């Protein structure tokens, strides 16, 4: 019984499956803050589902066979190109950013659909609430145009308003000199081209805008790099939270049913990420999009709705 | 017709013109709508009572009950309009111009 | 509108010119008043006097067209000695179009109005001659 | 809205309409309209925003005014005939008042101003109800009182509606406003033929509802409410663009599609009554509708408008909206002309 | 039988006002169908003569219609005098 | 197992399939019975 | 042949349309051998003049 | 097809079409009379049903 | 009758044949609906869900048959009413006196 009003009427109400362990946790930080490692330990210790940070190929991981697709089917967004040539005339910088916000929006919907359907909490690394720090850094460094920022805010305005914020926001605060040292040690040739000014912009946006905003409506825990090493103390901090803020206290079965109907319908989730605002960075001409869409339908198991693809082994198609 | 009907119909016309000629307050227009109901109730009751249409004696009550329910819905819309804008002025309800 | 239209269509064509011109001026004026009423209601004048000015400008314009159509169409029928001729109405309709090209001052509008008001006037005369019904009474 | 409450509210919208259709008493007809208006308001308000609140208020004021005028007509009719039976009215002033009230309820010109605004301000599913189910009750009363309607009044309303609907739609980019002006134009054909053959009124109403439901359902399927948003359909659901093209051409009255049938039949009935100018004027004026229907086909199906990069993410997910009855309605909306003689079932 | 009995004891302890309301409303719906006196309310209402009893023209074949009010034909209110 | 997430229509809904075919069979049997009954009533009423 | 069965579609359509065209003639026999111009007595073995 | 078949098939076609044409003219004439006089099944608009009337003796005699 | 889809008097008429061309078209419309249902949901158009495609045809045919029955009945009633009215009022439908073209004068309009 795929979830709907009928399933809701018959007793599939979110408050039944939810507990005081049903929480949405997001770990934030600058680049190379060990936030990935902290996020895994929190999930393991608290028995939550861990979501690796949503990258360029997150949506591929959730559809088809789950393996990544060729680049042209993500529009040719390259994080490596962003580092090598952040000011490329092709518009890769904002096109990557617009794609990544949509990837995070989809992931936030999956995480919320997991929380509401099973009751198990989730741990995310960054979210649609903190995606803007990279946009602010890009703009302040002159990588993207003012019009791109306006487009981003338009898309964020009509999308983020539908979703509840995280229960707990965890911030791992690492200074830019230490961030810059860990980057050079990580030995990724493109990442080492990152400059401290860009990194300082991310930090400023996090502390100037993100943390004050999330503090009003969420539980914010901030750890230095050293303190994040003590994951057990981090988990201990989380379990002693009062939770006396935000909209999660206003939710009831009727509102959570409306929320679940949204997050399960992924096209409804992504509706406004393609608003017809003709920004050159994200606009694709008819001939190209027609050609790429035709190639996409030729990929294995993509021509038809899932379960109706004989070319990947589906059977009983004439009774389905 | 009888002399009373002249003024009852006049009252309905006066309230209809009041309803169609808005000022600023939505409540003032809702009062005119109730005025039309009251004149309809009187005109119906007079006609029914004078003609001794016995089973029709309940009709004015049904008119009153249903129109009061209508007015309750109208008031609820007024307060929602007032919550949005801080007043019940009709000039604020012009978003759907475009 | 019934009675005014009854006075006009009772007078024989090509005769009693002053009565025909009065009937069309009243018809034209009434149309102007109706247009002014809706215009003032839906596009609120900036002031009381602007609205009065607009009412006069429209009403006078509409009465001007009505007067010229009635006079010119009655003068033509009288002079040509052709009462039941749609051409007379075609002439009067274009005259009205010119007036509307003058009040709005636009040679293009006048030329377009004369053709279309001229054609429309001729069709009205044909309809009267042959009993064309616009709002036909139900019969089957 | 709680799903059980939504169902009960929807059932009450239908019950109000059914009471109007089965009633033989004017009081019960009035009650049906009041019950129907009570239940419709919550579905206009259900998305809680200032535009929805403005739309519901404008709707409430229009419909409550029309219902008071209807009650006045009923009471005048009572004084001059001493009875309540739903049928011809026995007083010309009562007939005018009831006709004007039903015109306001239908959103016919010059009482049309609320239709584009209310439709714009409510969700697509609510607009679908407003422009289809809500026409049933007022039309079913006109069907019964027409022997006493003033011919000049009803035909003036019809002509004005076709003109205002055609002209008003030329200037619209919002899909909900286009459907609203299209509805005003189509109400004009329904009432123009009513004095001559009410069966053709029913035929035009039924075909209008089928075609209108098809358009709204296809708009809902893709969550499109603007012309430009609809122009991205070709890059997501190409099949939908073709179905929209067929439905729009049908709504334009082009043969051999279904939407030609009502115009064809209405012209026939009017000419049988020696009405020649009015049908010809109506048919030419309806070309204005065809124009702004064609404009939509150009930006949706016959050309490929520019896309966005994020559209690729949509390629990986299937349509999940219900699209109830869409396959059936699109076939009826386009392929019914060969069955035209079936209209006699409506007699 | 017992789980319902354990249910009633809980509402009787927690919401005696609501238990009494529902109990009274149930008796108001049920008892009229069980009462042997309910049938008399119909008869008494019909026995009350609000308007004049218009006499029938006698055509010679109405032996069940009294000629005089004090004749023995027609409905009797002896049942009502005892009640 | 190709799909990473099991598709909602991976396997047929046999109850729905059974009802769907059963409904189609019923309508055809009913339609033929109705037509047969209509033909006889017509022949009887017209004396044929 | 699963590779060349589509080539029967149009030829079969012609045969079917031919058959249906002949079927229509059977509904239009009201005046068969009854026109003033061609009416004649039947040949010994003939049942109808045309079909 | 021989000429005789086409010729007599034409006559069958003409007979049907002429019969339909006459009926179309008759129907328009019947509709005109029925609507003008109201004495036929068509254009029969309802009047109050007389079975609704109560004929029993009333509280007062003059009615 | 009154609010009756097929009144009892309709049973005196021949039923539509199950091979009626109009009923075949109705079945064809149901088949087209089945294919569009596959298309809008991105299933193999011709092969997917033959059970669903079968019910589309059956539903259309089933409803179409009764609609065709009512259609033919209404037209039979129209003719019944018309002929009975022509009989009731012989004064309004007299037999026209027919003249041959030898007697009827028609003006000749040369094309030269
Ligand atoms: C029996 C029949 C019924 C009997 C009724 C008897 C009277 C009893 C009371 C009835 C209720 C009346 C309600 C009046 C009302 O509330 O209107 C408020 C209405 C608007 O209220 P407001 O917000 O306070 O603004 C005031 C002005 O509009 C100034 O604001 P503005 O921003 O609009 O300023 C620009 C001004 C510009 O004014 C103009 O330009 C008008 C020029 C027209 C020249 C001709 O625009 C107007 O005045 C609006 C009207 C425009 C004219 C519309 C076409 C006429 O004010 C008026 O319009 C005053 C009119 C009052 C006259 C009442 C006469 C009623 C007769 C009905 C006809 C019966 C004949 C049969
Ligand atoms: C002569 C004039 C021109 C022709 C007139 C044509 C008038 C329309 C004819 C009726 C059309 C009804 C639709 C055809 C049925 C095909 C749908 C189907 O196969 O559903 C199988 C249905 C579910 O199949 P599915 O996988 O959900 O997808 C089917 C469509 O997508 C289902 O998608 P859907 O959203 O469109 O479902 C519509 C249907 C709900 O779907 C149904 O269950 C079909 C029910 C059709 C009832 C047959 C009506 C004829 C009998 C008259 C009484 O709604 C209803 O409740 C029926 C109204 O299986 C059943 O339960 C059979 C019904 C059991 C009773
Ligand atoms: C814009 C063009 C409108 C035409 C101008 C109005 C006009 O001249 O006619 C007024 C019309 C008179 O109609 P009337 O004579 O009363 O009865 C119908 C006779 N077949 O009045 C009417 O009854 C119809 C009113 C028409 C309103 C404009 C449409
Ligand atoms: C029922 C019987 C009613 C008969 C009358 C029917 C007329 C109803 C008209 C409803 C539509 C009104 C909206 C409209 O037509 O536009 C309003 C228009 C405002 O514009 P305006 O001031 O006239 O010109 C300036 C342009 N630069 O101003 C107008 O055009 C108003 C005049 C419209 C009527 C002619
Ligand atoms: C554009 C928008 C406005 C639409 C045009 C305005 C209408 C123009 C009407 C012209 C007059 C036609 C007419 O009304 O004829 C009526 C008359 C009916 O009389 P009846 O009783 O049936 O028979 C005896 C004849 N008196 O006699 C007839 O019925 C005969 C007329 C047959 C039908 C005429 C069809 C319309 C003719 C007007 C269009 C012709 C020009 C087309 C040009 C288009 C070029 C692109
Ligand atoms: C013959 C025409 C048949 C028309 C059938 C139309 C069915 C609706 C179209 C399917 C679209 C998907 C759907 O489920 O309908 C949407 C709407 C519910 O709204 P939605 O936002 O989708 O979810 C509700 C949660 N609040 O659901 C609805 O409210 C249905 C609205 C349509 C009802 C009016 C249909 C026209 C009148 C038909 C009567 C014919 C006489
Ligand atoms: C007795 C024989 C009658 C022959 C005449 C029939 C034509 C008249 C009826 C037409 C009415 C519309 C019929 C319903 C449309 C069904 C076709 C369709 O919608 O799917 C197109 C499909 C595309 O191919 P596919 O790879 O399957 O991709 C599916 C995309 N969702 O296409 C396919 O590959 C599936 C194979 C069948 C395709 C049929 C396409 C018909 C196109 C008709 C266009 C409209 C008429 C002009
Ligand atoms: C671009 C074209 C746009 C559309 C143009 C449409 C034109 C339609 C033609 C106008 C309608 C016919 O016009 C109408 O015909 C009838 C004929 O019975 C006339 O009928 C008149 O006949 C008698 C005597 O002749 C008069 O005394 C009387 O006043 C009036 O009844 C009307 O006075 C006239 O108003
Ligand atoms: C005997 C019949 C007599 C006729 C009675 C007349 C009709 C009265 C109808 C009243 C119906 C009220 O129905 C009422 O619904 C709610 C459902 O949330 C139930 O109450 C339920 O929700 C409340 C919270 O509000 C919980 O604390 C409670 O544990 C739970 O029982 C009531 O147990 C039930 O009584
Ligand atoms: C949400 C919906 C709520 C609906 C609630 C409806 C509840 C109705 C409950 C009472 C209905 C029956 O109530 C009572 O039953 C007895 C049956 O023994 C009826 O019958 C009794 O009175 C009649 C008089 O008419 C006698 O002829 C009869 O001998 C006697 O048994 C009563 O006339 C009726 O007053
Ligand atoms: N331009 C851009 N880059 C992003 C965005 N999110 C992540 N990235 C990049 O993704 C890369 C890796 O992300 P991180 O998780 O922060 O680095 P990490 O060292 O692997 O993980 P941590 O140790 O926890 O900090 C970085 O180079 C980021 O610049 C974004 O929204 N915009
Ligand atoms: N009111 C009208 N002008 N037309 C109309 N309904 N005429 C009645 C004539 C008619 C026509 C078709 C059928 I089938 C039937 Cl049974 C009766
Ligand atoms: Mg990481």
Image (spheres, coloured by chain):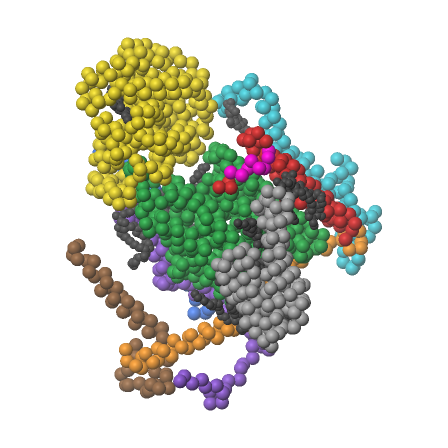
Please give the name of the residue rendered at 36% of the width and 39% of the height, measured from the top-left corner.
A276
Which chain is depicted brown? G
Looking at this view, is D279 or D18 the one in front? Answer: D279
Relative placement, left or right, of D259 versus B24 is: left
- Residue ranking furthest to the bottom: I102
Relative placement, left or right, of C37 versus A31 is: right
Image spot of residue A11 (x, y percent):
42, 30
Which chain is depicted yellow? A
Range shown magenta: B88-95
Image spot of residue A305 (x, y percent):
28, 41
Which chain is depicted green? D
Which chain is depicted orange? H
Which chain is depicted purple? I
Please give the name of the residue rendered at 40% of the width and 85% of the height, measured from the top-left corner.
I112
Res. A265 in view: no
- Quadrant assignment for ligand 11: top left
Image spot of residue B77 (x, y percent):
57, 35
Which chain is depicted cyan? E
- The correct choice, above or below, for E23 with respect to G29 in the image is above
Please give the name of the residue rendered at 57% of the width and 71% of the height, measured from the top-left corner.
C88
Res. D79 in view: yes
Queried whether the magenta region covers residue B91, the answer comes back as yes
Looking at this view, is I65 or D336 the one in front? Answer: D336
Image spot of residue A112 (x, y percent):
36, 27
Q: Colour of chain F?
A: blue
Residue G1 image-quadrant placement: bottom left
- The correct choice, above or below, for D312 with respect to D197 in the image is above
Relative placement, left or right, of A204 versus D146 is: left
Queried whether the magenta region covers residue E74, the answer comes back as no
Residue A21 image-quadrant placement: top left
Q: Colour of chain B?
A: red
- Please tell me how many numbered marks the rendered image carries: 0
């Amino acid at each position: 019984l795929q979830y709907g009003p009928l399933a809701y009427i018959l007793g599939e109400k979110a408050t039944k499956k939810m507990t005081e362990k049903s929480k949405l946790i997001t770990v934030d930080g600058n680049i190379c803050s060990g936030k990935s490692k902290l996020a895994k330990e929190i999930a393991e210790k608290l028995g939550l589902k861990h979501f690796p940070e949503a990258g360029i190929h997150y949506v591929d991981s959730t559809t088809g066979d789950g393996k990544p697709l060729p680049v042209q089917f993500s529009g040719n967004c390259s994080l490596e190109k962003f580092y090598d040539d952040p000011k490329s005339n092709d518009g890769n910088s904002y096109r990557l950013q617009a794609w990544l916000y949509a990837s995070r929006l989809l992931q936030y919907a999956d995480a919320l659909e997991h929380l509401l359907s099973t009751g198990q909490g989730v741990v995310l690394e960054r979210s649609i609430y903190s995606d803007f720090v990279f946009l602010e850094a890009m703009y302040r460094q002159g990588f993207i145009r003012k019009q791109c920022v306006d487009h981003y805010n338009q898309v964020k305005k009509v999308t983020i308003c539908e979703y509840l914020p995280p229960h707990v926001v965890v911030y791992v605060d690492v200074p830019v000199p230490e961030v810059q040292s860990r980057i050079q040690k990580k030995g990724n040739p493109h990442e080492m081209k990152i400059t401290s000014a860009y990194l300082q912009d991310i930090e400023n946006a996090y502390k100037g805008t993100f943390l004050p905003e999330m503090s009003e409506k969420c539980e914010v825990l901030q750890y230095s790099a050293w303190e994040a090493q003590d994951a057990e103390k981090v988990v201990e901090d989380i379990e002693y939270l009062k939770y006396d803020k935000g909209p999660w206290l206003d939710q009831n079965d009727r509102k959570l049913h409306k929320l679940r109907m949204l997050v399960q319908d992924k096209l409804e989730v992504l509706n406004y990420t393609s608003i017809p605002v003709f920004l050159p960075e994200v606009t694709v001409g008819a001939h190209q999009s027609d050609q790429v869409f035709q190639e996409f339908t030729e990929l294995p198991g993509r021509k038809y709705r899932a379960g109706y693809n004989e070319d990947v082994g589906d059977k009983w198609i004439w009774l389905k | 017709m009888s002399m009373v009907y002249m003024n009852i119909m006049m009252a309905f016309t006066v309230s209809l013109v009041g309803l169609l000629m808005y000022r600023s307050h939505l409540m003032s227009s809702l009062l005119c709508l109730e005025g039309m109901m009251l004149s309809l109730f009187v005109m119906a009751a007079l006609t029914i009572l004078n003609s001794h249409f016995t089973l029709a004696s309940m009709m004015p009550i049904i008119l009153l009950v249903f129109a009061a329910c209508e007015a309750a819905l109208g008031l609820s819309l007024l307060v929602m309009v007032s919550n949005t804008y801080g007043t019940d002025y009709v000039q604020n309800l012009n978003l759907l111009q475009c | 509108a019934k009675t005014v239209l009854r006075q006009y269509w009772d007078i024989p064509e090509g005769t009693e010119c002053h009565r025909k011109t009065y009937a069309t001026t009243s018809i034209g004026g009434a149309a102007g008043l109706v247009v002014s009423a809706y215009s003032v209601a839906l596009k609120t004048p900036t002031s009381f006097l602007e609205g009065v000015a607009r009412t006069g400008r429209y009403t006078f314009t509409a009465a001007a067209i009505g007067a010229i159509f009635g006079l010119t169409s009655c003068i033509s029928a009288q002079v040509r000695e052709k009462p039941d001729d749609p051409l007379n109405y075609l002439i009067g309709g274009c005259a009205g179009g010119l007036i509307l090209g003058a009040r709005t001052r636009s040679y293009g509008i006048g030329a377009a109005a004369c053709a279309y008001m001229g054609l429309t006037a001729a069709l009205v005369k044909m309809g009267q001659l042959e009993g064309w019904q616009v709002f036909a009474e139900p019969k089957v | 809205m709680n799903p059980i409450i939504f169902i009960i509210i929807l059932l009450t919208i239908m019950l109000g309409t059914i009471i109007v259709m089965i009633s033989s008493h004017w009081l019960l007809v009035w009650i049906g309209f009041e019950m129907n208006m009570l239940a419709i308001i919550p579905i206009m308000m259900k998305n809680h925003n200032p535009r929805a609140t403005e739309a519901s208020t404008k709707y409430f004021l229009t419909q409550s005014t029309a219902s008071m005028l209807l009650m006045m007509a009923v009471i005048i009719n009572l004084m001059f005939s001493g009875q309540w039976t739903v049928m011809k009215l026995f007083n010309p002033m009562a007939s005018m008042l009831m006709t004007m009230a039903l015109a306001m309820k239908l959103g016919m010109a010059p009482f049309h101003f609320w239709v584009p605004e209310v439709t714009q301000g409510i969700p697509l599913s609510s607009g679908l109800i407003l422009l289809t189910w809500q026409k049933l009750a007022p039309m079913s009363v006109l069907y019964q009182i027409f022997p006493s309607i003033n011919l000049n009044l009803i035909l003036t309303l019809s002509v004005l509606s076709i003109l205002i609907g055609g002209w008003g739609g030329l200037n619209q980019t919002q899909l909900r406003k286009i459907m609203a002006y299209s509805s005003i134009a189509h109400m004009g054909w329904m009432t123009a033929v009513l004095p001559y053959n009410p069966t053709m009124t029913l035929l035009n109403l039924i075909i209008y509802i089928i075609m209108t439901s098809t358009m709204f359902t296809m708009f809902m399927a893709n969550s499109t409410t603007t012309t430009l948003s609809l122009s991205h359909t070709w890059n997501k659901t190409p099949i939908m663009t073709v179905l929209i093209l067929a439905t729009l051409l049908s709504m334009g009255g082009l043969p051999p599609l279904s939407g030609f049938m009502p115009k064809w039949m209405i012209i026939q009935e009017m000419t049988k009554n020696n009405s020649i100018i009015l049908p010809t004027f109506m048919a030419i004026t309806a070309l204005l509708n065809l124009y702004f229907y064609m404009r939509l086909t150009y930006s949706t199906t016959l050309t490929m408008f520019p896309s966005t990069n994020n559209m690729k993410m949509k390629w990986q997910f299937p349509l999940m909206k219900k699209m109830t009855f869409l396959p059936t309605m699109v076939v009826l909306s386009t392929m019914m002309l060969p069955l035209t003689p079936m209209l006699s079932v409506l007699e | 039988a017992e789980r319902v009995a354990a249910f009633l004891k809980n509402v009787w302890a927690k919401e005696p006002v609501l238990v009494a309301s529902f109990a009274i409303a149930g008796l108001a719906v049920i008892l009229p169908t069980l009462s042997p006196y309910t049938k008399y309310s119909l008869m008494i209402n019909r026995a009350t003569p609000y308007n004049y009893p218009v006499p029938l023209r006698d055509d010679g074949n109405m032996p069940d219609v009294p000629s005089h009010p004090q004749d023995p034909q027609g409905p009797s209110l002896e049942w009502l005098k005892r009640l | 197992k190709f799909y990473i997430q099991e598709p909602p229509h991976g396997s047929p809904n046999w109850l729905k399939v059974g009802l769907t075919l059963g409904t189609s069979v019923f309508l055809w049997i009913y339609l033929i019975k109705q037509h047969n009954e209509d033909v006889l009533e017509y022949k009887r009423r017209n004396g044929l | 042949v699963r590779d060349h069965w589509v080539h029967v579609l149009v030829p079969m359509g012609f045969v079917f349309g031919y058959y249906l065209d002949r079927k229509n003639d059977e509904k239009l026999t009201a005046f068969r051998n009854k026109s003033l111009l061609y009416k004649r007595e039947l040949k010994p073995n003939e049942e109808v003049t045309w079909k | 097809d021989g000429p005789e078949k086409n010729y007599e098939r034409t006559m069958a076609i003409l007979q049907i079409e002429a019969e339909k044409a006459e009926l179309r003219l008759k129907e328009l004439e019947v509709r005109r009379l029925m609507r003008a006089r109201g004495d036929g099944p068509w254009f029969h608009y309802p009047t109050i049903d007389k079975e609704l009337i109560d004929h029993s003796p009333k509280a007062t005699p003059d009615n | 009758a009154t609010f009756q889809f097929l009144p009892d008097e309709a049973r005196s008429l021949p039923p539509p044949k199950l091979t009626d061309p109009r009923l075949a078209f109705v079945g064809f419309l149901g088949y087209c609906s089945g294919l569009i249902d596959n298309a809008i949901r991105r299933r193999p158009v011709l092969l997917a869900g033959l059970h669903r495609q079968l019910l589309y045809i059956t539903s259309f045919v089933f409803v179409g048959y009764y609609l065709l029955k009512r259609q033919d009945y209404m037209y039979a009633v129209r003719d019944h009413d018309m002929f009975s009215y022509i009989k009731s009022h012989p004064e309004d439908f007299p037999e026209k006196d027919k003249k041959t073209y030898g007697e009827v004068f028609e003006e000749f309009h040369p094309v030269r």
